[PDB]
Image 1: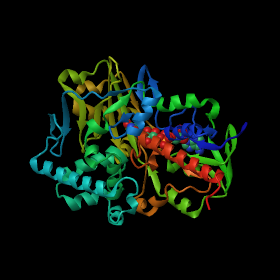
Image 2: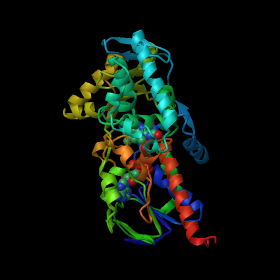
Image 3: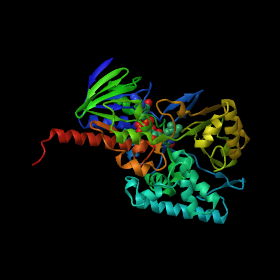
Image 4: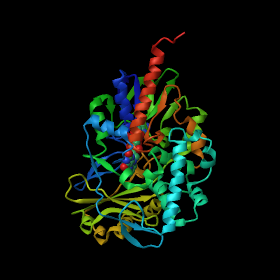
Length: 459
Ligand SMILES: Cc1cc2c(cc1C)N(C[C@H](O)[C@H](O)[C@H](O)COP(=O)(O)OP(=O)(O)OC[C@H]1O[C@@H](n3cnc4c(N)ncnc43)[C@H](O)[C@@H]1O)c1[nH]c(=O)[nH]c(=O)c1N2
């Protein structure tokens, strides 16, 4: 049982907590990072499964994510682009598989125009409302008390268009059904990425990856922090008063002046607070939940789809696997596909045995890229739902109505206790870039709090 004294304790060694920790040390404050798992990285994790390197969690970098990109440059990390040559596959409402190129689905002209209409409206809302305080906008209550499902249908009678547009947010981002989150929540997602248009473009949101894996972002920061990072040490209790904390984890107890809960909001209540958090937090914390998505990994002897002039990209609002992409590692001679099974469809397939689920998922992928898909050398499902220190994927969002109700307090410190994760971010919301931005912003706030306590207040 280590017994440490530090300026700041950070709960969780994901990218948010680790970024905050480095920024704190840089500002002259000592830190300790207490991590539950036997590794750093949190929702980012590179592992080798039966001889195949896979990114089990977060991996994509988009062009809006300049903060993450600066960090990559500082860490000496390099990026590469997802393969996108050739034709993509779309399976529409008419059940027809059609290959295509360009920035437009091969849909009828009415559906194409309805999609453009919806996207333009959403782009305008995102620009008006912004990703920082969506809850504060005059349109917040209107937009946050109707589901995205119903909002779409108030604005278009075209079911195929509505389902496609829903796909980019529901299955694509929040990993919850469109009837379970609000239009305002969709607008926040869009604003956080620079526009709704950006979310519709896989060449934007799924543009690049980090050579060697996204987990390096955490691994390298942790290596630099040395044994200020304690692994296999879940935080159980935070005793606090107005002036500091004693944080009790399984392998270390740390006395400090501040603590950062650098964990997804659904896991806040895993920590006992003495005294309890205020009623506001007690309530707010219950109204948040992670989505659910199965990240499917299939490795083949070669990227077979390229032989047929396909990019490996596939979309279908109606399929079991709604999205598939080329996810071949930089320099690999084998080929890797990644597919996504979201929310209620994930529930459904989790009903099946592992064997039957694999079969159904591969058959769905074959629907896009052909029967070679049926027989990978390695098949693996990211299973973040089973992880007690995550419990879902990709990220947390409020229940319907919760964003405009609680958003204004999501960043509020409780005395010495701060909250920091990608789930709370504006730009980069729910993504590693957001995690990094939040780590930086929270460290800055603590630095400023420290400065106010140490510099005599002006007359
Ligand atoms: C499968 C799927 C795929 C993707 C992604 C995730 C998931 C799993 N995402 C999202 C993404 O990775 C995520 O936003 C960040 O990893 C979050 O960083 P945080 O540090 O904020 O939380 P994160 O969950 O990563 O870290 C929190 C940490 O605290 C720990 N912890 C929790 N409670 C604790 C306790 N009581 N005591 C001690 N430790 C505790 C955990 O074990 C963990 O390491 C993504 N993002 C992106 O930019 N591009 C992408 O392509 C993807 N794709």
